[PDB]
């Protein structure tokens, strides 16, 4: 077993206090609905089920700092509504998309623990979705050093190719 | 071959390497990277403890590679380990105190995927999947879906490197 290394109510959203778990689910769903088709494709790729899209977006956002996810919450707070039973996302045209809170809080807990129900393996695609965020963040962190960026790409490329060969 | 390591002309043990490397990460990793790798809500000592045990799990080849790349940002003195950030600011840590904390950190068994080094994390996932794909008791349909989904995830990951 493995899990996302980033592990209540200490966040605020539309005048109400919420958990980090709720914030992560809200921000992931809002991105799912309102990111441009191009940004969504670049972020998670194509051919995923809606629940798997959420899982991969969730673990990327669950790694954000408090500071950065509070900045996100502020930017999108007016687009979201957390009710007793639902998380409701409004798109740029005013259409509302309802997501069952229970259902997505359970999906989120699966994803944070990299669990696949009924399958004896870590959720490898979700773990790789998280590692993509690690890579993207480490790459920005080198952008004033061509050497450090090259070493990071070369070392990661070697590892990802070794992992390709294992499946070939 | 040298049993210990060389840092800025000084012979240092793996214990010192692990502590230097973890402290350099703590100081110079972006807050975004730190959150991804160890989470938040940790005290300053606990941040180091988590970073220590994670870097201690890196192979010698990978840690010796890291050591070379950070050597220009670190200094080991009798009393202190000194980390310099990209702005020239110096952050100093009592060397004996943090070597002692490191011995305690070595006792931690953390559940998070260890991603202070991305190849290390990918090697863990590769091993875990190889095991699952070989235990043919369970569902062949499940295994073929997992293999297909993982290949697609690897292809999406690869795209970030071009």
Image: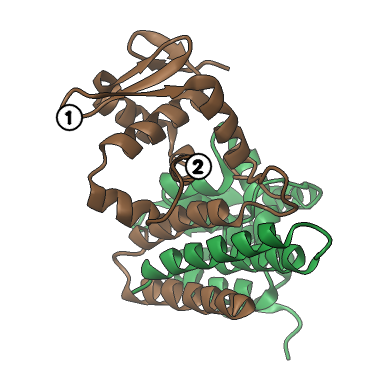
Chain colours: A brown, B green
Front residue of this view, candidates A75 and A68: A75
Front residue of this view, candidates A148 and A71: A71
- Disc 2: which residue: A55
Residue B85 makes an appearance in the image:
no
Q: Residues within 10 Å of mark 2 (few under 14, many from 20)?
A: many
Furthest residue in direction bottom, as rendered: B1
The image shows residue B136 at horizontal and vertical percentages of 80, 65
Furthest residue in direction front, as rendered: B141
Circle 2 SS class: helix
Residue plotted at (79% across, 57% down): B138
In the image: residue B105, left or right of residue A31: right
Circle 1 SS class: loop
**Vertical placement of B60 versus A8: above or below?**
below
Question: Which numbered disc, 2 or 1, marks the residue that appears first in the sequence?
Answer: 2
The chain ID associated with circle 2 is A
Please tell me in which quadrant of the rendered image residue A4 appears: top right
**Vertical placement of B133 versus A127: above or below?**
below
**Vertical placement of A12 versus B88: above or below?**
above
The image shows residue A54 at horizontal and vertical percentages of 45, 40
**Vertical placement of A45 versus B1: above or below?**
above
The image shows residue B149 at horizontal and vertical percentages of 54, 60
Res A92 label: 1
Q: Residues within 10 Å of mark 1 (few under 14, many from 20)?
A: few
Inter-mark Cα distance, 2 to 1 = 23 Å
The chain ID associated with circle 1 is A
The image shows residue B106 at horizontal and vertical percentages of 78, 52
């Amino acid at each position: 077993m493995a899990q996302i290394p980033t592990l209540l109510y200490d966040f605020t959203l539309n005048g109400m206090t919420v958990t980090r778990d709720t914030v992560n689910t809200v921000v992931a769903l809002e991105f799912l609905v309102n990111a441009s088709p191009d940004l969504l494709s670049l972020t998670i790729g194509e051919g995923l089920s809606e629940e798997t899209k959420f899982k991969h977006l969730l673990v990327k956002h669950a790694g954000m700092t408090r500071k950065r996810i509070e900045e996100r919450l502020g930017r999108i707070s007016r687009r979201v509504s957390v009710t007793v039973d639902a998380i409701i996302i409004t798109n740029r045209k005013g259409q509302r998309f309802e997501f069952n809170r229970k259902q997505y809080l359970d999906i989120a807990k699966q994803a944070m623990k990299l669990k696949l129900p009924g399958i004896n393996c870590v959720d490898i695609p979700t773990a790789l979705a998280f590692l993509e965020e690690v890579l993207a963040t480490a790459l920005k962190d080198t952008e004033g050093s061509q050497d450090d960026r090259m070493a990071l790409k070369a070392d990661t490329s070697a590892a990802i190719n070794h992992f390709r060969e294992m499946l070939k």
